[PDB]
Image (cartoon, rainbow, N blue to C red; front, side):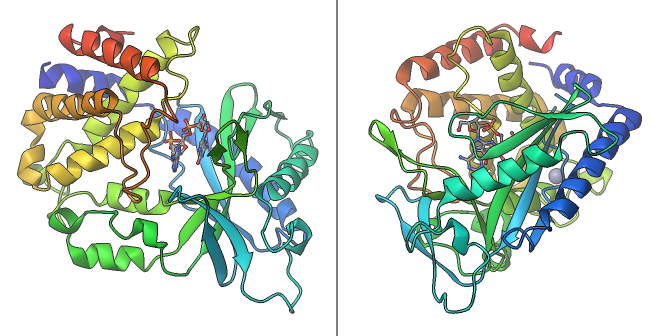
Length: 359
Ligand SMILES: Nc1nc(=O)c2ncn([C@@H]3O[C@H](CO)[C@@H](O)[C@H]3OP(=O)(O)OC[C@H]3O[C@@H](n4cnc5c(N)ncnc54)[C@H](O)[C@@H]3OP(=O)(O)O)c2[nH]1
Ligand SMILES: [Zn+2]
């Protein structure tokens, strides 16, 4: 695949400043309103907007992703069934009145109740109280996000998150292997930042827990993504222009297009851009030098990514970049047939100069 061809695709994928500014304006308004009103509850009084950038998320330009962080003080986690990613939330001391005490189902903080209250407050307040027309989508299966549709054209996913300024869980110890890439110093200062928790329940055979939370490091992902090169001046000049972000955009667009084409079937529904992002991070670990990401070698680099991703589909092994023992492509999460299907489609695309980019 020619580099100029891929860069022609990415060239034709760039959206105008107006289309971004308008939607960003509407979403900004709705988000500010929802936040200001969310602060009317004692539980969500300390709510706050988490800066994930709200951009570089969809390649779908009408889809946004905002995260509502909620500050919780000195929480104690309990790893559930050694899933390494899902935990129970407890509080060290509750003699002092706790805003979230209403959601306590014993000593364990109920995620489903918090999500229910959250979604209910939002559902009540979105009823045209603003000047914008907003509606709430149907409750998704096992999704922590509350999605809203604005003007029947804009999609906004709102995910509640508990912020813990404590040290990261032991399951993340062997994760974030960015030492040879972004230096151990940067890894150090990154792990000093807080970590988040989203209301995501874990699978227990033929049942669900609805009381567990999952680890989230979206802020860390944004940080390492926007500061990606080994050299501090990476992509700040003509001599040090790389193609990392370009590769990620291309991969995301590939998966997006394949999911779209095969929307009628349910094969590619379980695959998400996070699998792509994770694979990209692992390739970034494998190729730490900026010289391995030269722009003229785009077509090469991208291929590499593709190959690796396919491997992950073939071997059914995609470790979480922060939680190495958490496999995203386990047979328990995604069935073999779906990954074989996706493998087939991606292989077809790669072998035929990617006709799925032609749209
Ligand atoms: N908004 C949202 N936040 C979540 O944390 C989340 N977890 C699951 N789901 C949804 O549940 C269904 C089945 O599980 C899927 O439909 C899936 O939707 P999705 O298309 O995946 O959502 C894309 C974003 O959701 C995030 N991400 C998705 N998976 C994970 C994960 N395992 N760990 C941490 N974050 C994850 C990720 O940031 C990625 O970024 P982009 O917006 O750029 O695509 C989530 N949806
Ligand atoms: Zn760069």
